[PDB]
């Protein structure tokens, strides 16, 4: 009757000679119905909600910074980062200040319910990635806001910008023209409130396990 | 090897002094791979499918009426409903005839696969919320239809209207102009059939547990 | 403390006199946190990822061909295929060369993370169904590409075409006009690489169980 572990090593594959187990800070809370697999780093005070799936078995590594949250049904996965010659595929590798990642999720970042960040991708600190939104082959700057159902594919979202709900951004020209987050923007304080809440949820939930 | 309960209390937090466990009608069926947490009310004959996540740990309470269904990977969650003074945040509280809710899902409502209703939100009786659709900060009337991939954010959808597939409705002006459901509309009988089916699935599945 | 099986029979219902258990090739890998229910056929070398839900309890049967993959949070489900007279509802039945299915997923097909194929539907061989995409009441040909967040509802996508990211195709006229996949198209080699990877992941993961 379905006996198993939800935090585990990635399997041996032609691009993964030696398996890795997730490296998770004692202060992070991983829901029992979340799945965390392979070459993953999870930082302090991170909340991982039911049904999230963080799978570092193809592209690796996948890093989630401190005080960030990975909400219900969020998926983190990436395109192959090493070839057949054990050759790093640089096109599928993201570089975040001297360190290489398949997926890099910064500090104080919110991955809201049912969103997905697929590598190669980087999401900078204090950014809110909206409900059902999508990031793939992109670098989202810090202090950004992806409204619900927006997407960034193959682009760089400059620091401090936002993507209106439903908008799919596929070109650098359009990413260059995004609106700026200002004090009066409707999602201007959303991330700070969410981060506050989720740090407190992680602690509350750690006291139930 | 991952030992746990999928129906459980919310954690103690600064806004939740005392934990609550879900209140679920004996005739509802909660799939073993669904997650139901915290201040939740689930009505009679409700079917909750694999991978759904109903989490009342921030905004609360979350109510699902009789004969409604919460399909695979559907997420129900809400913005904080109480502040730091144990102060009710009225902007994040929905009012459904004398009673206050973070998320209110009426009777005979279908939350189709991978949709999401995030509070503050109310969905009126006999409404079909389409596959992958999204409701957030909105009141959807009764006898409505959100086609697949449609969304209602920050609006009121009048009774008897529908939102074409893919359409993101963010303004009251646009919500005011939605088309009416008529006998010949393609989704006119969709909800009644779905409700019929899911009430019967709940009973069938209850006989397997 | 939540004791259960993730691969199981569908329940007895008015349209399902006798329950069926999934028929899964020994070489397929079904993640322990995936759910597979009812009248399902899973072919060889298929990888089913965490949080996927394949549920054949309404419309049936649901078939997934050899060397195909059903990624994280993907949902497969279908509209009722038999009435009250045990009457086959031909409108909700798809025909794939002499055999009838509620959902037919061909060989070497990739159902990428958080996508969904809802029957009646057929997806032809070597097609990539993008992240968060949607197929419902449609026949997607072989060698197609649904980019991330695209959708096909009520149409036939001819062989060798693609749907740009975010595009919702609801009419045969628009499906007739889709662009062709060519050697230089950005997703032209995507499916073959994904299929290669997932066949190898299935084998790797089978060696961990
Ligand atoms: Zn992937
Ligand atoms: Zn939420
Ligand atoms: Zn369905």
Image (tube, coloured by chain):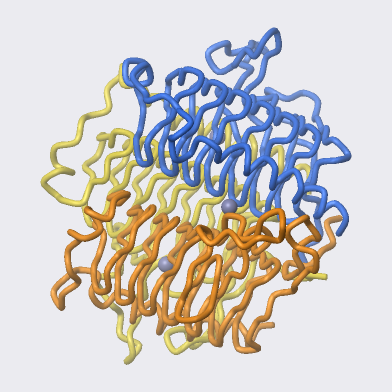
Chain colours: A orange, B yellow, C blue
Q: Nearer the viewer, residue B32 or C103?
A: C103
B109 left or right of B205?
left
The residue at the point 47 percent across, 78 percent down is A68
Instruction: Name above or below for residue B206 compared with residue C127.
Output: below
Q: Quadrant of residue B208?
A: top right
Residue A120 seen from this side: yes
Rendered location of residue A147, percent (x, y): 30, 60
The picture quadrant where one finds residue C93 is top right
Relative to C184, B5 lies left or right: right
Location of residue C200 in the rendering, given as x and y in whole percent from the top left corner: 76, 48
User: How many numbered discs, if any?
Assistant: 0
Observer able to see residue A74: no
- In the image, A79 versus B196, the foreground residue is A79
Residue at the image position 62 percent from the left and 47 percent from the top = C71
Provide residue C59's location: percent of width, then percent of height.
63, 26
Q: At x 14% / y 50%, what residue is drawn?
A: B172
Q: Position of residue A200 (x, y in %)?
A: 48, 86
Residue beneath the point at 29% across and 57% down: B97
In the orientation shown, which residue stands out farthest toward the top? C98
Asked whether, in this view, residue B144 is left or right of residue C42, the answer is left
Position of the N terminus of chain B by quadrant: bottom right
Residue sticking out furthest to the bottom: B85
- Which residue is at the front of the view, C7 or C186? C186
């Amino acid at each position: 009757v379905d006996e198993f572990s939800n935090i585990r090593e990635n399997p041996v594959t032609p691009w993964n000679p030696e398996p890795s187990a997730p490296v998770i800070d004692p202060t992070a809370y991983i829901d029992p119905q979340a799945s965390v697999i392979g070459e993953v780093t999870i930082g302090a005070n991170v909340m991982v909600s039911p049904m999230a799936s963080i799978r570092s078995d193809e592209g690796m590594p996948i890093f989630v910074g401190d005080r960030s949250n990975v909400q219900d049904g969020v998926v983190l996965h990436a395109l192959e980062t090493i070839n057949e010659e054990g050759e790093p595929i640089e096109d599928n590798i993201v570089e975040v200040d001297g360190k290489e990642y398949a997926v890099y999720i910064g500090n104080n970042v919110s991955l809201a319910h049912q969103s997905q960040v697929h590598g190669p991708a980087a999401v900078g600190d204090d950014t809110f990635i909206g409900m059902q939104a999508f990031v793939f082959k992109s670098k989202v700057g810090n202090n950004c806001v992806l409204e619900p159902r927006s997407a960034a594919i193959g682009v760089t979202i400059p620091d401090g910008r936002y993507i209106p709900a439903g908008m799919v951004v596929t070109s650098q020209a359009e990413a260059d023209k995004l609106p700026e987050v200002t004090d009066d923007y409707a999602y201007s304080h959303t991330n700070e409130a969410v981060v506050y809440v989720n740090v407190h949820l992680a602690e509350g939930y750690k006291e139930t396990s």
